[PDB]
Image (spheres, coloured by chain):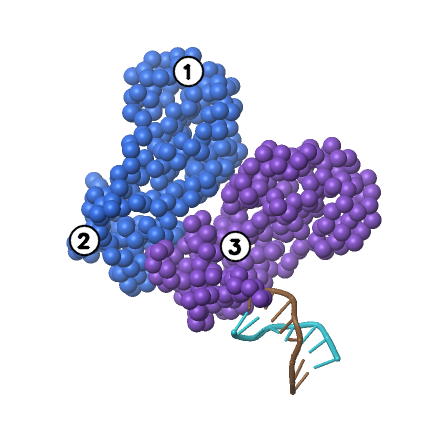
Chain colours: A purple, B blue, C cyan, D brown
Amino acid sequence: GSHMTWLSDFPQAWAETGGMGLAVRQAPLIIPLKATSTPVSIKQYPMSQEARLGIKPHIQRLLDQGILVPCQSPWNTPLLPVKKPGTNDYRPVQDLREVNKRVEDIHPTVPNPYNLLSGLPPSHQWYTVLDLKDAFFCLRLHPTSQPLFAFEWRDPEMGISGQLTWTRLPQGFKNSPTLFDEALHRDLADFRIQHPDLILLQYVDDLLLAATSELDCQQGTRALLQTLGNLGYRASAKKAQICQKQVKYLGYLLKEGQR
Amino acid sequence: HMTWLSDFPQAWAETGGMGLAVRQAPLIIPLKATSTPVSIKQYPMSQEARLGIKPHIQRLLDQGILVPCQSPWNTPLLPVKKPGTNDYRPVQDLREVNKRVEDIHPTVPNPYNLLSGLPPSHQWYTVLDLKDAFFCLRLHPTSQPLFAFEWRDPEMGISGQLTWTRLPQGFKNSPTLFDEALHRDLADFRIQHPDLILLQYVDDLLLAATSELDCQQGTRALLQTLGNLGYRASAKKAQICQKQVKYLGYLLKEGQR
DNA sequence: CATGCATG
DNA sequence: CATGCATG
């Protein structure tokens, strides 16, 4: 149709119009520690006022959304101000290595990008590719697990005088990809059943919907967006590839052939 | 009916846990322009009272509804009672805090004027009350300092104060902020169900339908919507699809009492 | 920045 | 054994 019509018919489905997501059907996650792990408090590396100002907006947006909350924890990991090469564009990166080492690994069951796409039958050649924005943040952390990802932050304006931590699955945590992948799979099982004429590929927060015609792809995408929104997820409108015979997915490019 | 608790896990507190209004962003509480922090010292309480209350504080702590803090503000924590031998419940005297917070217009219905506008045509009702309603709304970090109170406890690792991360009890504007929050959230539901009459008084709801079937279809949709929005109803108190129910202290069968 | 590992 | 760099 247009892209704008897609934005208009599904405001709750896109991160750009429906605010940040939160998976309503997902119970708070408990992060099991290794049998012998004990809290570790890695001190915050000194940070220049310039770098701090540079990442302040990132922290603020999260605080305003309740994604970051104040806490007092025996755990602590460094907050790193990563500045884009040749610019004054900063972004925060939390070094969670010491926490990851004390958390038990979860054998990732995420499918191989290649096989996933290699299964698509030649009968379904119309595609819609979406990627959920701030995916991990849509999954809540049980309060007993929140203390694990604490970091230092100071700002009188926000009434923060010590530490903050995440209420959602953090970026940088080793099991986030698989935990999210499994969550979205559970949440989309119903959709798959309601649409036997459609193929749905999903790799963590990346989705590819395949149909036999532009019409079926159109109607399937409407259903998918409505389902994702109701479920509490948010797709990136700016990056979406709706109803095309040629799309980019998981690094792979599929036109009527592959990459 | 046992299908209600099995079919709608997210809508009931028992199966869905502490709620959290997903459409409602953490709340900022505006202080009056003249206001200044108030520090009221904690009145010492019997070691027997600090026991019957200890569990509450602990439970909130563990759910993250309470958090340690250092704040310029401080209000009393009162050891209330009950007929029982050891039934002490927390009561925070937020009066000095309320006097310093900017007032907001009362938008809550008048109790009775709510039922007065109830068509005789709708005689099938469902009464639901939301559990821990105010707690579904979060407090922005910037406004959390306002509600702090003293609890030095070695056992849990508290060196001084604790404060709320959710809309607290005793805060003058809690009833109004929740009522307005729930009203906005259930608006789409009202529009999509014109043949249904929905009354809302803070955390007390009453759904009215023309027939038993309509009530059941309506109730299923309401619970589904509440769950998705993050609210939680008390399945234990719920009166589902029946012509005689009690709502807002009003007994209403086929003739209001 | 800190640094874990595949890599020669 | 030494080290480039992807990733926290």
| Label 1 and label 2 in one chain | yes
- Which chain letter goes with mark 3? A
Horizontal side of B133 relative to A36 (left or right) equals left
- Along the line of sight, which residue is nearer the eye, B34 or A42? B34
The label number, if any, that marks residue B40 in the structure image = 2
Q: Position of residue B3 (x, y in %)?
A: 51, 31
Measured as percent of width and height from the top left, residue A144 is found at 44, 56
In the figure, is residue B104 to the left or right of B22? Answer: left
Residue position for label 1: B123
Looking at the rendering, which quadrant does residue A104 occupy? Answer: bottom right
| Viewer-closest of B164 and A8 | A8
**Element class at badge 1:** loop
Q: Secondary structure at mark 3?
A: loop
Report the amino acid beneath label 3: Leu
Q: Residue under label 3, please give it.
A: A169
- The vertical placement of B97 against B115, above or below, is below
